[PDB]
Image (cartoon, rainbow, N blue to C red; front, top):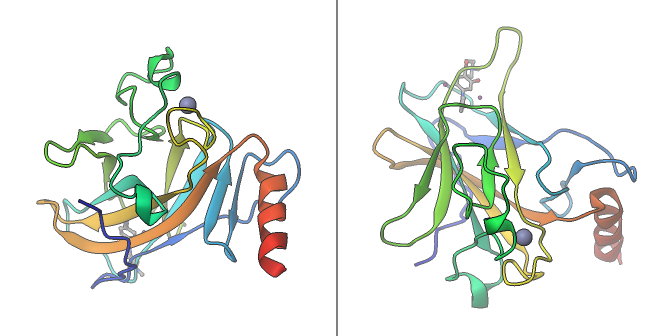
Amino acid sequence: SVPSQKTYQGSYGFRLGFLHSGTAKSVTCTYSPALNKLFCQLAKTCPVQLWVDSTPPPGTRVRAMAIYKQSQHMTEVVRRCPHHERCSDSDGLAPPQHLIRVEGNLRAEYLDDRNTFRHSVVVPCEPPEVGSDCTTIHYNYMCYSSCMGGMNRRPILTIITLEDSSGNLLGRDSFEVRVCACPGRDRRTEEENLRK
Ligand SMILES: CN1CCN(C(=O)c2cc(I)c(-n3cccc3)c(I)c2O)CC1
Ligand SMILES: [Zn+2]
């Protein structure tokens, strides 16, 4: 009743990568390697790189799912709060309850698991554009970490899985996420707290 978060490169050497966006007050998405934590504003583009050592088979897919980080909340489905699930912000593909969306990919599919009720969004693997060495998926997080009746200040993890055409596991990586108004300030604060 809890998805695994164990990092697993698998046969294709799968792992994530993040840009270096800095901590200026204006930054909208910034990743802390020291915390393995992405800080982002509500509904803003979060570029996540996908890296492999070798090409996975045709029909391989990449799925994203959120879980609560704290063990005492891990069995609770992460969903949008009672306010945001009712706001008129649909993109025509993502169900209004889903926290994580993929931006700019008409082949994205959204799953409400019939057994666990967890939400996820999955896209087909596509090779990098000519001249690039990795593929980037653009995610959006559709609720603040602080939203009452939803995440309610509880930290979450995003689990990214590489899957075969039947959904079997080929690779896994993960990162913590805080969705907040000032990601640059919050990253600096939490990195300072860690250094102390
Ligand atoms: C050194 N080799 C050069 C040739 N490779 C690719 O073109 C490649 C193919 C795929 I499909 C993907 N891909 C994985 C998940 C989503 C897209 C990626 I990231 C790639 O780098 C593999 C690595
Ligand atoms: Zn919300």
